[PDB]
Amino acid sequence: APQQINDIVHRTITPLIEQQKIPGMAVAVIYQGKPYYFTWGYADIAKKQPVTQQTLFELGSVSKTFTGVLGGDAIARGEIKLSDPTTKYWPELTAKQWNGITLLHLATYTAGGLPLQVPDEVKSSSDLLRFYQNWQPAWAPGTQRLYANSSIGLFGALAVKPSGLSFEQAMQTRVFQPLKLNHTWINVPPAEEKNYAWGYREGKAVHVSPGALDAEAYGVKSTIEDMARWVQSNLKPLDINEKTLQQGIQLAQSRYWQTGDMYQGLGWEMLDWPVNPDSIINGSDNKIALAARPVKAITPPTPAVRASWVHKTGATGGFGSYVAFIPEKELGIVMLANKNYPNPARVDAAWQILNALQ
Ligand SMILES: C[C@@H](C(=O)O)N(c1ccccc1)S(C)(=O)=O
Ligand SMILES: C[C@@H](C(=O)O)N(c1ccccc1)S(C)(=O)=O
Ligand SMILES: C[C@@H](C(=O)O)N(c1ccccc1)S(C)(=O)=O
């Protein structure tokens, strides 16, 4: 590999792994249309299985970027509009607080205080309906952002309804397959089980537990190679042959809301490049990232801005991931680990690497 890339990546990631006690890690740097891969440690400690370029990691909330692009593709297909009322796609949602809550609000966490999690007690479809029917907003729509699986997860479920496809079938056929992400999964198939890393939490091997809206909010598993291809697809949407997917990728990077110095896309979040590293590093801490914050509407949304830092953190109980890229520089990074270690450590490492290369 180019020595600059080798050195920049190793000098940043080796200490990170040591400090954070990460059992296994894979990193991709995407530099001018080419990926460079690096791996460390163990996918399975007990079985002594190393992390390889074929190891599957749980992406956790990085999955929301796939959800956002799938939703973008459904808009491009003319199947949904972000301006449509939620009730158009879920007519059983008759409670009055839903008047004025659109798919845009669901997609961007601005419905007015939908909770981070769907309650664990929600086990059935009828339970889910009751939950949303009985939910009371703290805020008028389009006024406060509160990061929420119950928000974007419902967006993903509704976005695919006109197609008649299940969320998994829509994702596979409309996103994974056209982009040749052949080792990216909502449900890991038996053929891939030998590559599926264990997550580690408090010294125990764990995989993500089933939950309502899991696929839509945090349920994708992928390899470092497929994730590098995902970054390249989001860096160069016009190279995608399928018109609706090409458009959907771009719609996910449109800037719909601003809070502080960040802009909310569909799944993706964006800041102007060059960024203040303190703002992305400190801003990534859950003390800010999961907080309720006022939003300014961007009226109308800015189309995807080339000079942006585009990124997403995400975790499950046993995994921690980060993806960031800068379209104007054709530059990106993917960091996948089988421990949920703090967001700011991820973002700090990514910025050190990308800043040294840009
Ligand atoms: C960088 C550029 C491209 O596709 O070559 N564009 C882009 C802008 C934002 C995000 C991703 C790509 S584009 C289609 O505006 O010219
Ligand atoms: C906060 C969020 C994430 O970091 O991806 N979630 C999480 C919460 C606790 C532990 C691990 C992850 S999630 C996937 O539940 O939304
Ligand atoms: C992330 C997930 C998991 O099992 O890994 N968990 C979860 C549990 C209930 C609802 C949503 C997510 S978690 C946060 O306990 O680790």
Image (cartoon, rainbow, N blue to C red):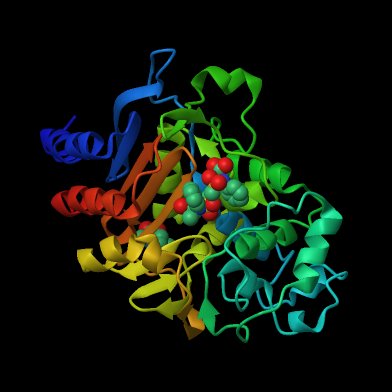
In this picture, is 205 found above or below 87?
Answer: above
Closer to us: 63 or 23: 23
Quadrant in which the N terminus appears: top left
The spot of residue 313 in percent (x, y) is 41, 53
- Please determine whether, in this image, residue 131 is positioned above or below residue 1: below
> Is residue 304 visible in this depiction of the protein?
yes
In percent of width and height, residue 13 lies at: 22, 38
Residue located at (31% from left, 49% from top): 332
Q: Is residue 71 above or below residue 9?
A: below
Residue at the extreme front: 202
Quadrant occupied by the C terminus: bottom left
Ligand 1: which quarter? bottom left
Could you tell me residue 306's position as x and y percent? 34, 66
Instruction: Specify whether 241 is left or right of 280.
Output: right
Q: Quadrant of residue 74?
A: bottom right
Relative placement, left or right, of 317 versus 75 is: left
150 sits to left or right of 260:
right
x, y percent for residue 28:
32, 38
- Is 267 drawn above or below residue 41 in the view shown? below
Residue 51 visible from this viewpoint: no
